[PDB]
Image (cartoon, rainbow, N blue to C red; front, side, top):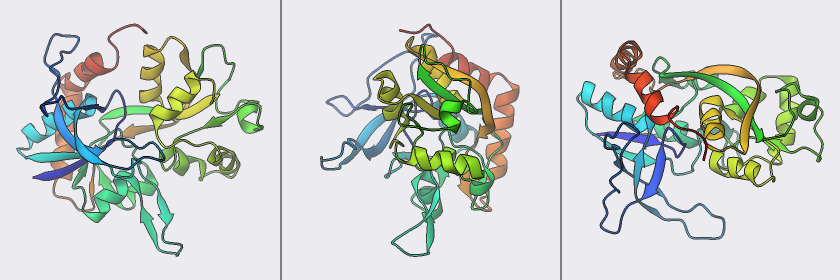
Length: 287
């Protein structure tokens, strides 16, 4: 039974409480089909000041449908859990030493806490040095989320390039955005500014933009375009930059790599991936 690690990230992975009896609410997609739900154990509340607890929760969404398809095609059983530290994954020095370890889903995959990462995980060179990725199951990039009416040209906008306390922007801590910005001298400076405002999760950053507490949120276009399409007060702006793909993550020399990429290829060929977009991404107006 493979240990699958994932993360809360709508519309790829929705996380909801189980009903009183431990089951997951019966819901249906836009096509009238039952929404497939899996039990995923993980931290409940991450609000600072309250005790942490890990409990069974209900997970569903684009990546869960993909997981179910992969498991069926490759004939494997699995158990899903949410990454304990709630992060995607960057490499940092730990324990005030020079020893480096990956946090987030990356860390759990490398430690053995997980056997496969099935989430909107960005394929990048930094991570590819430590793990193996399947071919992309989704093609996307980075963009910027702002409140409707906010005027930003894109990543090269002066309010981003020449930061001040008048226009606050940020991303989610320990994600691929960090990795990207540390690759350029100029972006490194900008990330230093962002470091003072980065959020723990995408959900919190998105809410901050709606509440006028964060002026711009730099993040994955697959997620931001969905969020903006569902909330009439939020829009994305600027040309996409740092185009990239999301892939399934496995440990180095994993015997699953070939077959996982094979399944993904077939899904891109037969309409399965496109159907997932029509089910989870493009299906209704904002409300």
